[PDB]
Image (spheres, coloured by chain):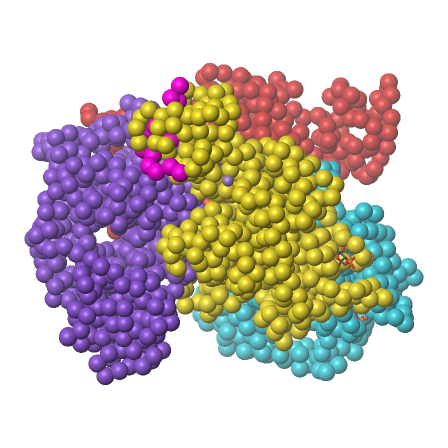
Chain colours: A purple, B red, C cyan, D yellow
Amino acid sequence: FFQQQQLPAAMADTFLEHLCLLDIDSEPVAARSTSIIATIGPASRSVERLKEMIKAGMNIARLNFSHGSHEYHAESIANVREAVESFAGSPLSYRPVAIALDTKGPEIRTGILQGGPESEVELVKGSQVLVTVDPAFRTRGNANTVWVDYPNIVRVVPVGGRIYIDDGLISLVVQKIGPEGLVTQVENGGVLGSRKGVNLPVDLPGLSEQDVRDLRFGVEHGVDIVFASFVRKASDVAAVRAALGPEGHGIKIISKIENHEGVKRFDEILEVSDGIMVARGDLGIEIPAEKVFLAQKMMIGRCNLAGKPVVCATQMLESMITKPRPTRAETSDVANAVLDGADCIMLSGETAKGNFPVEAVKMQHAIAREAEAAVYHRQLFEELRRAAPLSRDPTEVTAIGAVEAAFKCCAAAIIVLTTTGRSAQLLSRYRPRAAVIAVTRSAQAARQVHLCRGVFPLLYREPPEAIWADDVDRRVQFGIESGKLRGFLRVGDLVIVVTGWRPGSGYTNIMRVLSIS
Amino acid sequence: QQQQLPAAMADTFLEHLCLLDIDSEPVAARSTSIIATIGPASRSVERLKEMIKAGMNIARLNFSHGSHEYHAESIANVREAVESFAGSPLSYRPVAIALDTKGPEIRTGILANTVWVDYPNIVRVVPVGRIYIDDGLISLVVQKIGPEGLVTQVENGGVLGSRKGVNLPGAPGLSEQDVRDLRFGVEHGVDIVFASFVRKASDVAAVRAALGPEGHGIKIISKIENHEGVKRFDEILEVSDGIMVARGDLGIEIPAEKVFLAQKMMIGRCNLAGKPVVCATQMLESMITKPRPTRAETSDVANAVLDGADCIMLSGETAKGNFPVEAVKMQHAIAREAEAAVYHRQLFEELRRAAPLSRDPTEVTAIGAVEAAFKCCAAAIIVLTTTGRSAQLLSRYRPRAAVIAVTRSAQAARQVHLCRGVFPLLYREPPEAIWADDVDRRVQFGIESGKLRGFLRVGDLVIVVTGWRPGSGYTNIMRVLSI
Amino acid sequence: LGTAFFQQQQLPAAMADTFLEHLCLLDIDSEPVAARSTSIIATIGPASRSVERLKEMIKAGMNIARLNFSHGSHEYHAESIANVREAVESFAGSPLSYRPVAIALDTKGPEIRTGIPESEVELVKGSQVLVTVDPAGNANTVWVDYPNIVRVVPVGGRIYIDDGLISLVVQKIGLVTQVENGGVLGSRKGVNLPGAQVDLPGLSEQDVRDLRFGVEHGVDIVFASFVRKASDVAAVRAALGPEGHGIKIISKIENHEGVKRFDEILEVSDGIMVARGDLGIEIPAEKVFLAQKMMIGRCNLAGKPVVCATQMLESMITKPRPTRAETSDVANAVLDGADCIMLSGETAKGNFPVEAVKMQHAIAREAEAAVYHRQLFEELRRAAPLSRDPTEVTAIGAVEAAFKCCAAAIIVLTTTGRSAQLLSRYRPRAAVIAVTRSAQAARQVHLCRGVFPLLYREPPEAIWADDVDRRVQFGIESGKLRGFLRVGDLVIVVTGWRPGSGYTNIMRVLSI
Amino acid sequence: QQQQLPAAMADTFLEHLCLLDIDSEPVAARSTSIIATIGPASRSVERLKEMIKAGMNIARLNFSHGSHEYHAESIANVREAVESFAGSPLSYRPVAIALDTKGPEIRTGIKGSQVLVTVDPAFNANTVWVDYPNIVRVVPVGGRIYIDDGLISLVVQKQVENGGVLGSRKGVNLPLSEQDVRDLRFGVEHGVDIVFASFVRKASDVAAVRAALGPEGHGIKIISKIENHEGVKRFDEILEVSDGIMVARGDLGIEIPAEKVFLAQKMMIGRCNLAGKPVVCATQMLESMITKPRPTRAETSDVANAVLDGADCIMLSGETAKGNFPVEAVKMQHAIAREAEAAVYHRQLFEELRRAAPLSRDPTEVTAIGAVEAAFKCCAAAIIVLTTTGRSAQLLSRYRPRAAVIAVTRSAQAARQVHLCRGVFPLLYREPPEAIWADDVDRRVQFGIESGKLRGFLRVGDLVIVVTGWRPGSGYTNIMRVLSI
Ligand SMILES: O=P(O)(O)OC[C@H]1O[C@](O)(COP(=O)(O)O)[C@@H](O)[C@@H]1O
Ligand SMILES: O=P(O)(O)OC[C@H]1O[C@](O)(COP(=O)(O)O)[C@@H](O)[C@@H]1O
Ligand SMILES: [K+]
Ligand SMILES: [K+]
Ligand SMILES: [K+]
Ligand SMILES: [Mn+2]
Ligand SMILES: [Mn+2]
Ligand SMILES: [Mn+2]
Ligand SMILES: [Mn+2]
């Protein structure tokens, strides 16, 4: 109890008094429920660096298949698994880490600039720039002319349209459509390098030939999660599932909502996906920048309703690419994503290319811990309660009973046994304040539950005891011992233990109140 | 749907009222206990058997009249009728016996105008500016305190005043008779005591001392009957097992149009504390003479259940009326409809937030069990309990599912009738050698009894609440089961 | 606000954040105000017919006099109307304390009456009994005033007699029955036939003459008995004619069909009466409170008056004090949201008609202070649709303003009563003092909870704005004299920008 | 469906989130005021006119830098740009001038674990100088001291957290000066409207500022900047004596841990909403737009979440003082604020504000809540209120009505000062009083209707709520009327 983890604010009767009672001297618990996804790149590739990021709090390593070869990414996977497994010799402190593959998706990139792949050229504001796809001008990239790697570009944009280059920094307005070149008037000028992104706010297919190879690669190397780029409809997810094949039927598909189409068809995309990523990078270019927060809050709420994980990504701590501490806007954005109900937060260039990858992970860890305590659980739990339909599934029934029991005694943890992760996910979807300590024998499940907020996975490695009830108790004790070592639990704490009545997944039906001795 | 389910789910209380349907039949068993007063109309063994089948749960002995031998016959006939069903343990219904004390009574003198009372401090307790006599018929105001006594100015005329009851509004805990009657109740093993005229905490402490250590297990229900008991209600409730709103005397001691305020205040505070509350007096008074009640009486019973009362009482309707069995049936039918019409959505929400954080594993398991019951609309919550406390902590959250309580204690089985929603089952088998099998047996006994009595069907979901070791106070386990 | 002021009117329970805490804070020492908002309808009969008796009940608080046309001739009811109006107008010499009293006509409706004169036949239970269509009554057979009764009732059907006290069962098959419940049988009592569809016309030909009588004598309200469908009321309005177009029609819901078709009945009616007497026989007694609470809530949603009637204080027909069930029934009807409460035999035949009125007055005062206005107002305002009518917009603003300062009253000027009813629609705690020049509006607004009508009798001032202020002042002086207002009280004043009905649009905060 | 009405009507906040629509366009004037700091990028009259048209409502003078003559030039340029629109009174936009005090600053002098700092006037990467003479009594053996906006830190040396390039004269942090007094006197002389009081730690700091403004600065609003741990702890006593609060995340983010700043922001905004007083969110809202034409995703959400929290004002610092896109940054804040104001869960916000607002017998307070309720009942296009000091407009703004509060006033100062209150749009009435007072009241009401029609607020057929008083002078507001245009 005490005056810690914003408990006075949690006991408020209105959201207004909740805000009034928030305290900067009320310290949070050590358990951080929002998972951190860190992108792998030249700054976070060495085994030595990855060990620091795992200790700092990185839960999922993201491989961005828009850059680098299959051989390059196989080296990233090997270095991650080498860093993760160096801690395995101490099972009570072992932290599982998931590997996520981010697909290239339907991209449009420019041509290499004349003079060198590492030289610059400027565009004049209000000038006249010609956009061409002619194969001859592929290496002619200059101030007056730019090449695009998308042939069917002249038959999609009307007169007066808009073409964005380099993360929406450069803007071109279509004036006339010419024979073998698109005449534009620059609307927003700026420096332009080589082979930058192009957004067109399309007939490029939903799943490319190269992304098919990329998905098979992820199955052969046993990735746990796929981030599918530019998901526009349900069949875009089915195509990714089909390319994964029966070999990868257990891989979680997280749909990236990156344009107006994805937001419009969100309901049909969410029903067929395991989760959603709000990809505010491209989404900030495909729809007006002042509206991205609407799309993020909408998508987070509907995922919290559905009980499916949602990832918030891009530019959360962007200034930390070059500076050791973030701006006030960036700290508030991470805190507010946690407040909205995000299950995971992501770092992109902050860990891939920046000079402070470990410090960015440490900052997200510190912010999320404070923000999680500031969640107004009293109204959140009540609303998730009413919105969720009645259930005859004993796992779901037990889950809500355990969460309510945890709120009643301010339990330090809910310890649940799970093989597939489902029992921990059904606890997570009701957003308990107590940490959900999930003890599993499945290494894959231990990595995959990082998607669900508040679930701390522990990989159990011992062969079964001869009496199953003894094997259950040993696993519960392993969760308590790990919680003690990691600082989640102390003597005298109350804990809720969630198990089933028989071995095998799907039989969870028991909730017990235990005190830590 | 049935059980007024469209109304119980409504977003607002106004929409809840709008959706109440007279064609939505009640399905759950009725959870408000019926207390019937024993009298000439309900003293024979065969009539008591009729009233048990009609839904009587507690037999009230009114010690305001009758000799000790008279009440011993009442106890023997009640126990004979109750035990005639013990041949079928799966359907046996325990019936509590409650002793209602006579309490301190100020009566006038025997043998004109300006009478005297046996209470000698009447001159000191009534200041200048009212005294009611004989059920409130005569009313006197005082305008001067002199050495002879009071002035006795007549405000309302009246007659018939030989040793009649005196009430003084606005202004010991146990008479010698109550001490003897309370000893009788211990020696005859009564389960509940209705302490009359409780106005402070020391009053119920004196009842406790008269019961002695031999009667430590008896429940003490404090009857609030005057203005002082209403204003010191918080201190009274703290030391009592429950409260009875005694509207009869309360309606004389305070203005009759204020009694409903006292009733709703006390029921709310008892609901808040998780303690049983009894609403009593003239609920179906016209049925003393007529076979059907008035519209006000039928509304009165329903509103007492809606207010949150744990038990409703019948006085002359069963003690001396011509339709004692029909009066019990009428209370049963009304209570069933009223319980389904409870706006359960706001009730459970408010009880949840008002109940404070607790680290007691029984309290933690209880709220988890009630939440789990709502999530699957479980047919019942089966709980094993030695003293009934585990079943009372479930009842305090007013679940819709029945709380089926399996106990070996015959006294605790009778006493849990005070808590709304608790259906006691008396287990009679001797303990198994291994304790975990004894627990399984009792849980299955509650299942099989629930199946016979229409509580449970094959395919239903039930919430079972047990503990990790024998003895009371260790409840900590909640399980979801299918029948 | 003054701390002593905060201790009355149950304001601590009003400020509670939950209904549970609202219950826990109710205080028997918290005294209410003198202004009771729930109107009292009293049935006129032998016990309440003398002019001197009507005077005592006006002072006791009777607001609407009910003529029960089930009994008595037109000449009987004309003398009743004359006596009521004489007692009412006897107070008109003092305008500031004049209490308008509405006259309500309760129709006979499709009734069925047993057989006869003042002897009494007891009836044995389980004795075979015949019901008689023959115009050619003992314990073995009795006759009835319905020739087509043999056509409708099936074998194994139930017939009720004398407030459903006696129940006949057609054990074999006029109809030879055997008795389910036996009792002392009077002369010409009531007969109810639940479940069986009767082919009796909702507007009989005697009903048409009674409604014409009410229009010719200028009654304000019609209680239409046994309304089963929307065109039952359209028939009543057609019988009233263009002359009776201003009479309020209250539909009495008395049987299962009326409850099932309640929504279409409410749409064409000015209000609803929960007629618990016949309802309690036509449907199981255990379900009446479900029907009462359903209709009160739906009327409160629709903003139309609802009356609760029958056996509220029934023991007071013979006793000077009611039972504890009766006092809580009145209180709970007010707590449910009823606009009006009714007395039947308590004032028509009983020995304590004035005391019954006084008892209902005292209970209503206590129960009105115990309403949880916080949730009631929030739910009424959330359920009411958005409006572009300035009268509705001003009304909700004035009620909210009255809650903010615990205003002693809302003073509204109204000619038709609509501005007062829209204020009453949102259930303010403050009394709605309605100043009107229309004597009929002053009578009919008693249907709306919380509205205290004042009849203004002066010719207009020549500047309309001054004429508005004189009526506001008349409202203030009247409230001061009746105890509703004191110096230093805040009052909300609701008026319009121009004369004529329909232009209310102004709310003002004034100190007394 | 427009302006997020499906989201605003929802029965639960969770359903409100699910119903937010990127296609639902805002159809309502922007209610959150924009404060732009004046500096080299925004001193020219031409740039100030573009920023006025872009949405700037308050011009901030940072007295941390620049002499009195530099700031007099800034005031003159702002007023010349503002008064350039006075030719059309129906569209004239008042702009307030706010003085931001220097406060008790500590600056440095004009890598390796050993570093010496000393206050010696006779004293590179090895030795730096500071201006604070003594500090040896405030720091214990546990605390630390920060250099250069928190980038370089040192514990009780008696060189942690790295520390890169350090320049000449940058801040020093430690987790009423004579200069401040002459600055506040300067502000009274030049008729500034608002004072931002730096580093307010207790209620007596506010009394000192009010004393330095003299009896001639009675009408100047004092906004207290909560900048450190003590200001957060004694917040309630500071709020009670201030006209408003600024959450100064810049310094606050160094004085307390950066991860805790959002907690302090939400606490102060909520308490200010409770007390009905204006609160400003400040510093680094759109920092990247100093060098880039478009903001980061974090910055867009940060401005939107400040509005959703309930801030009455949002601030721009280097984005408008020194950046390369000062007009575009104002345009961006205006655009984000409009979208976020429609996304507010008005159903629960209005309910919680009304139940938290205590009962009152003041007729202005009673009229205000009646008018806001009336506005909700008809979706009034606006609430037109006549006011001399602005108090009647502030009492309406307290309840956060959906309708715009059009405040008509003769006081040029009050017109500028009500910009601190969210949803208040001031109009300055210039005509002289009519002979009959009632005609002068109606003509001001019609002035607000005419101005509202020209600006797009009002439209023929719309319903409006008009709030007036019964006698001249302030404090007598007591009338609410429903009118058709
Ligand atoms: O002088 P009049 O004609 O009585 O009008 C005064 C009142 O009539 C009103 O229009 C209200 O009347 P209604 O309630 O019948 O609509 C207002 O203008 C004013 O309060
Ligand atoms: O908001 P404030 O400062 O209290 O001013 C409100 C005042 O404006 C008025 O409407 C007009 O007053 P003036 O004619 O003096 O400008 C007064 O009735 C009212 O008291
Ligand atoms: K990608
Ligand atoms: K009738
Ligand atoms: K400054
Ligand atoms: Mn992308
Ligand atoms: Mn008694
Ligand atoms: Mn009838
Ligand atoms: Mn600062």
Q: Taking B208 as reference, is B377 left or right?
A: left
- Magenta residue check for A176: no
- Camera-nearest residue between A102 and D64: D64
Q: Quadrant of residue C425?
A: bottom right
User: Start and end of the magenta stretch?
Assistant: D153-167
**Farthest-out residue, front:** D122
- Magenta residue check for D164: yes
Q: Residue at x 76, y 51 (%)?
A: D475
Q: Residue at x 26, y 82 (%)?
A: A178
Q: Quadrant of residue A489?
A: top left
Can you say whether B338 is above or below C67 in the image?
above
Q: Main secondary structure of the magenta part?
A: loop
Residue D329, percent from left and from top: 46, 58
Residue A268 visible to the viewer: no
- Camera-nearest residue between C512 and D46: D46
Residue A210, percent from left and from top: 12, 63
Q: Residue at x 75, y 68 (%)?
A: D443
**Farthest-out residue, right:** C93
- Camera-nearest residue between C152 and A93: A93
